[PDB]
Image (cartoon, rainbow over all chains, first blue to last red; front, side, top):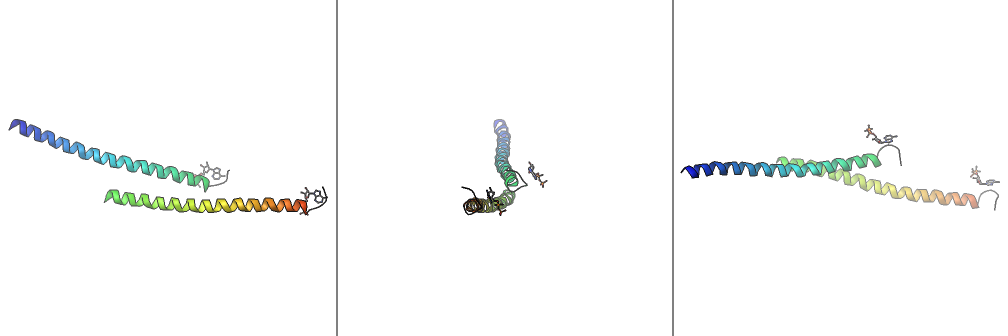
Length: 53
Length: 53
Ligand SMILES: Nc1ncnc2c1ncn2[C@@H]1O[C@H](COP(=O)(O)OP(=O)(O)O)[C@@H](O)[C@H]1O
Ligand SMILES: Nc1ncnc2c1ncn2[C@@H]1O[C@H](COP(=O)(O)OP(=O)(O)O)[C@@H](O)[C@H]1O
């Protein structure tokens, strides 16, 4: 009974940990994509910008 | 829902980027052609020009 309820709490912490990691992965990747969009936009600002070469 | 609407915005930026690049390619090539036309015209001004050799 003691080992079971201890384990149940540990299991709950495990579920929470997994959910947070899943969220972090999702966020990480969208940020890489958003960073790349910004980089691409900057290069278009260069080419379709002012005067230069 | 959150990831979807984020992605939709990112997708819109992607479409815009692609359109601008397409325009830049079109413009680039016509300019090379116009530059070549100018060069050719200059050589005809030379040959069918004034006096020389
Ligand atoms: N004569 C120019 N006019 C505009 N931009 C130039 C010129 N020469 C170089 N640039 C480059 O283009 C960018 C123009 O600055 P930016 O702040 O992007 O324009 P804006 O303030 O109109 O958005 C600069 O980062 C600069 O490196
Ligand atoms: N005696 C000449 N008469 C006219 N052009 C000459 C003569 N000798 C050399 N040229 C060459 O031909 C060009 C004539 O100048 P250009 O401004 O093209 O003529 P226009 O002013 O009549 O259009 C010059 O770039 C020059 O290099």
